Image (cartoon, coloured by chain):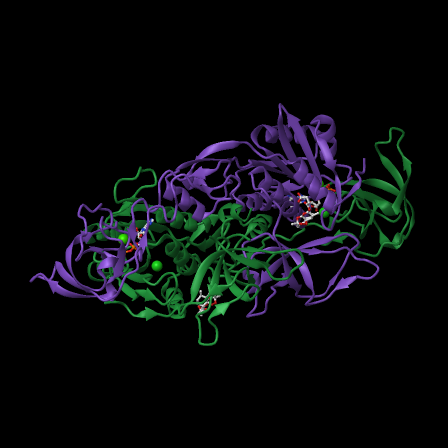
Chain colours: A green, B purple
Amino acid sequence: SPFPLTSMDKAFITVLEMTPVLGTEIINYRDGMGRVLAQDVYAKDNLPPFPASVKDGYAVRAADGPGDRFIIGESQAGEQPTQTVMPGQVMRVTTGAPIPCGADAVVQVEDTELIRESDDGTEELEVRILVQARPGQDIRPIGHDIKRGECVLAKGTHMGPSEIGLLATVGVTEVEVNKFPVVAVMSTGNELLNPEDDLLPGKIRDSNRSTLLATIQEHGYPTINLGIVGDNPDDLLNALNEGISRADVIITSGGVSMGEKDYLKQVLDIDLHAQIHFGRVFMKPGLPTTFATLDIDGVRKIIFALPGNPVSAVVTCNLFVVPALRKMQGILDPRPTIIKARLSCDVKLDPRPEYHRCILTWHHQEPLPWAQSTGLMSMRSANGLLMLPPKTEQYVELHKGEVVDVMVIGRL
Amino acid sequence: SPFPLTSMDKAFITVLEMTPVLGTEIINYRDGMGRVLAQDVYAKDNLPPFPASVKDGYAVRAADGPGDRFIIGESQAGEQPTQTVMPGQVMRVTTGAPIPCGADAVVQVEDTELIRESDDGTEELEVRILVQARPGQDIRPIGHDIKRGECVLAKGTHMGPSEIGLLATVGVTEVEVNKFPVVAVMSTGNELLNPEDDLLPGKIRDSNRSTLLATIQEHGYPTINLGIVGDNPDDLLNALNEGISRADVIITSGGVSMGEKDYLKQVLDIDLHAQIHFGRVFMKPGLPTTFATLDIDGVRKIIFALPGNPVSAVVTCNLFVVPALRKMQGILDPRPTIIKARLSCDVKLDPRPEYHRCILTWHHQEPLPWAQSTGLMSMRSANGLLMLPPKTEQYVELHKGEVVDVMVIGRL
Ligand SMILES: C[C@H]1[C@H](OC(=O)CCC(=O)O)O[C@@H]2O[C@@]3(C)CC[C@H]4[C@H](C)CC[C@@H]1[C@@]24OO3
Ligand SMILES: C[C@H]1[C@H](OC(=O)CCC(=O)O)O[C@@H]2O[C@@]3(C)CC[C@H]4[C@H](C)CC[C@@H]1[C@@]24OO3
Ligand SMILES: Nc1ncnc2c1ncn2[C@@H]1O[C@H](COP(=O)(O)OP(=O)(O)O)[C@@H](O)[C@H]1O
Ligand SMILES: Nc1ncnc2c1ncn2[C@@H]1O[C@H](COP(=O)(O)OP(=O)(O)O)[C@@H](O)[C@H]1O
Ligand SMILES: [Ca+2]
Ligand SMILES: [Ca+2]
Ligand SMILES: [Cl-]
Ligand SMILES: [Cl-]
């Protein structure tokens, strides 16, 4: 089988439709970066749990109005006050300290003048309140920010630092989340040497394994290095079986064209009994990209057999593998972010949709970024993939300045 | 000292000007994600190191033209050929295999017809070449992609997956890079409990430590958890001394206003003998944000004393701390990426420049993203910080749809 040419849209949709969502596990909240909640999270306490001052100043009775007041004590952060403010009295407060019984407003220190103090100046005795406070001013009532019983995070939330801080706030230190996929990577070819090797006749160094592993690691997922596998079916089958045992996802590169020494598709079908959903994609680069699933004991393994050309391998990894991994780790909409950018140079269109790494840059006050195709600008890694449309009889070329879609693949 | 109000621009520039660049170390290339090269990197081999076929097909003499040819053997990937192609002969080749002596072009299999084979069909014997090849066609000459002696990566390059793959390609498996900063984080306040604690009267859980540690970890830097420190100068000094010993950067939160129990600025100046460069910033939120340096034995430590309010702490961490850490790890221009976005709702301007977390979203074919201020949209973490200008007599409010600056703080 020279597999049918699959459209890019059909290939991508097929990857997402066929990729499973992984099961769940309980983690410590500090380990939650990039995880997706598999439970709703509720507050068991009010925040604040006591009425809390917003200001350094004095807790007062608003009904007393402005005037001169006896200071009966201080409320400091972390201590519950024991005294009750009666008419004509106030209590000093600091930001975050509890409001004492009998007070209903806070007056910030700037709206006061101190009018009696102890001889040694350490104890405030009488203060002039210069304003009419409104009841409740500069107080966070109990539960103002979070109420006991409130759902503070919904299942499906993809967590970042602020969500971790919210779990800390509410004391929910263990949470149910989707698992991350474990991703195994192998390279294929009799010509490949390890990066650590000196060259030998007829040989080159394996770069795809490093590039692909780094790409997956950049997204936070655990990886397994399956090494270099020669161009023979027995070795390929054994390496695939090891990947299936050790990982949720297997990525290979090389050996997927129709060459005399290309065995991977035959091994996947006849030996592994995997279901190849597509074996060619009408895209540039990436024609021989292959995607398969394997259902064993009610678990679905997914296999990407990427082209061997290094540029093709990293482009197809970003287009197909990353969205699948995002679905596996529970992200509800796992699709890439697409930004509109201006082409930095003219480009010829191909009958196939074309993809190329680029750098996105925003310029002073200009609203749209520019996309500069790769290959001081060299100090930056690629953070985008230009997505060029197929040529038509009408449109054969795009011009500098014209707006194109760019897929985000790195931090901007 | 109620410290002077420092403009945002002066505060930010001061942080970057006063922050050092860390020294260098040698790392394994697989550990290079996010590192900055401190050396130029050179290729010691050509790529390809032999003339390499781009195609499955036949190595031919272009001068023979089209016609029927004897196939004298095969060149397979990873094997140096030993035979010389003479007039009237060709050799089978596969993609990435070396071109044999005597051949000067490759004809892809699609431009041929097989016209003699062995009885068992395993050996090709004669092929009809249907095209006139151009000399050099479908061959990558030695060094076409990389030449021995070529600088392939310059010092100052901020590495991603493709740079790691390039180090693998050229066999440079150990590289000199800038160190990453080690960042210590402490929280302050007598009211704070650990996230793991049940509440006690007058107390709340410490969230800032978790949020700040997660923010720093998201950027890839090692962290040290200095815990909760009470509101007293001895304990604050001891915790700062531990941070200085263990880390390059110390982040505190809380205790930086003028309150009765706020000691940190006094401790930094009088006890630690640090140089406080600013102690207030004209910004909303973040008024009491403080930045200090401490020079010990020719090493500069940097200290950020952030406000205690949780929103203020995470906003000021993203504005001031992250750019400093990027400078420390060697990034040449460590400043944030600013994108233009449309406001999703009307906003009132303040005399101070105002900052608020938001979510940036790109809509179908609309060129500019929308910025939706925080507090299915809830499934996403904040990836931006709205940067609102100070009000003027002319401009008091911004309206839905108007374009504003947004600082990127998360993956888009
Ligand atoms: C065909 C459409 C797909 O559409 C679906 O996947 C529908 C089923 C589903 O949403 O699961 O989305 C994708 O992702 C973005 C956000 C950009 C990237 C594009 C992919 C690179 C190609 C498929 C295309 C693509 O366009 O839009
Ligand atoms: C005042 C200018 C500063 O300008 C310098 O830092 C000049 C000295 C130097 O470049 O080192 O850059 C910054 O970073 C961006 C990219 C956006 C973020 C802004 C900061 C939030 C505030 C400072 C401002 C800022 O605007 O531009
Ligand atoms: N891991 C790798 N690192 C670098 N180059 C590779 C790697 N794997 C394959 N290549 C190169 O990519 C090209 C395409 O290889 P491949 O996809 O295996 O084609 P075929 O299936 O026809 O052998 C060849 O030049 C090959 O040497
Ligand atoms: N680590 C923290 N976690 C959550 N809230 C905090 C933290 N530190 C301080 N806060 C709260 O932030 C607010 C401001 O505190 P802070 O900056 O210490 O003010 P002051 O210096 O006046 O005591 C208070 O409500 C305080 O309880
Ligand atoms: Ca191969
Ligand atoms: Ca405090
Ligand atoms: Cl390809
Ligand atoms: Cl603040």
Residue B49 to residue A355: above or below: above
Residue at figure coordinates x 46%, y 69% from the top left: A389
Number of numbered discs visible in the structure rendering? 0
- On the image, the x and y values in percent for residue B272 come to 69, 27
Q: Is residue A156 left or right of residue B352?
A: left
User: In the rendered image, is residue A325 in sight?
Assistant: no
Q: Is residue A3 left or right of residue B213?
A: left
Which residue of the protein is positioned furthest toward the left in this rendering? B119
Q: Determine whether B128 is above or below A375 in the image.
A: below
Q: Residue at x 53, y 45 (%)?
A: A379
In terms of depth relative to the viewer, which is nearer, B377 or B155?
Answer: B155
The front one of B242 and B343 is B343
**In this rendering, would B294 be left or right of B411?**
right
Q: Relative to the observer, which residue lies in front, B312 or A176?
A: B312
| Image-based side of B145 in relation to B177, left or right | left
Quarter occupied by residue A268: bottom left
Q: Residue at x 34, y 38 (%)?
A: A196
Q: Residue furthest bottom?
A: A393
Instruction: Answer yes or no: is residue A105 visible.
Output: yes
Residue A70: image location, x then y, percent: 88, 42
Q: Return the residue found at the far front.
A: B63
Residue furthest out toward the top? B297
The image shows residue B173 at horizontal and vertical percentages of: 39, 37
Q: Is residue A303 above or below residue B290?
A: below
Residue B307 location, quadrant:
top right
**Quarter holding the N terminus of chain A?**
bottom left
* Residue B132 x %, y %: 26, 64
Quarter residue A361 falls in: bottom right
Q: Nearer the viewer, residue A90 or A214?
A: A214
